[PDB]
Image (cartoon, rainbow, N blue to C red; front, side):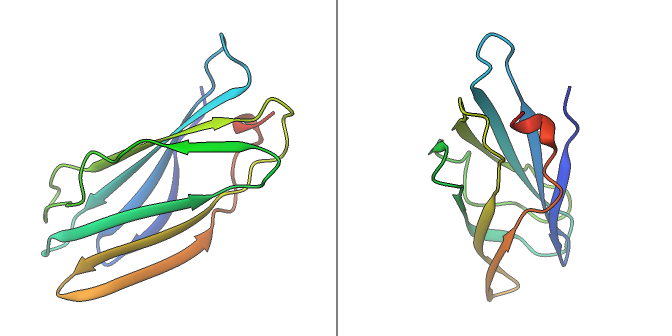
Length: 120
């Protein structure tokens, strides 16, 4: 089992990666992103876009929603299906956009510290 990885925090809003490598399909990696909000203000219009090396292939599922309510409200989850049969090193760049405290938030960053286990 591969442990989660916190990849982003800003003013109570956090993003977290979970990983699953199903044994019955070695080529496949399932990444679930989870957005939580422990601030005093709702997060709205939450969108997460992702990019990966051309050496592998990615398909996104629609997220569970676009709103993360204040004070430990229900999270947003989004699944990313990754096929990496050639076992190339995974790299992951995310673009986050959302509204929080009536301000437009825009953040972009590559995820460091991705476990080798997620692509090996």
